[PDB]
Length: 49
Length: 49
Length: 49
Image (cartoon, rainbow over all chains, first blue to last red; front, side, top):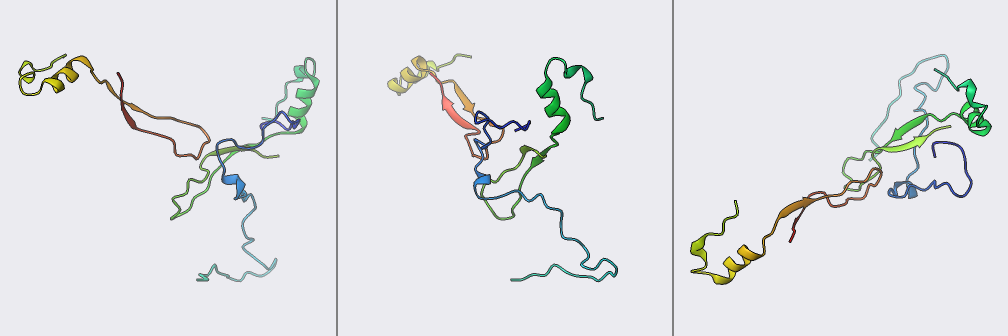
């Protein structure tokens, strides 16, 4: 809803899209690019399968 | 750019309060999958607070 | 442009009668919705009488 008013007459369910029934949005910042504040070491995304 | 007109807490107190103190930040959302054939949300609209 | 060939109620009476008296008017149909993710008809074909 475009404004933060919630009084049982507002509809928050997307009427014509059922994707949110099973999939949540990911609004997180990505992984941190460094797991050490002082020293830089390369790490990788690897294929697990 | 932050502008809530001063001559608005004159005719409607609550609306001016809501606009001033609870801003909205509209954005559009979508998902992509490579070999899906399922519809999935493409250009949803939401308001982040 | 209204043309049913005169040398057609010679070899096929019923087809000529149908073409002459019950014309067709083809057209294409579709629907649009903003936040659907449902397929919905896009370019159907129909014949209006």
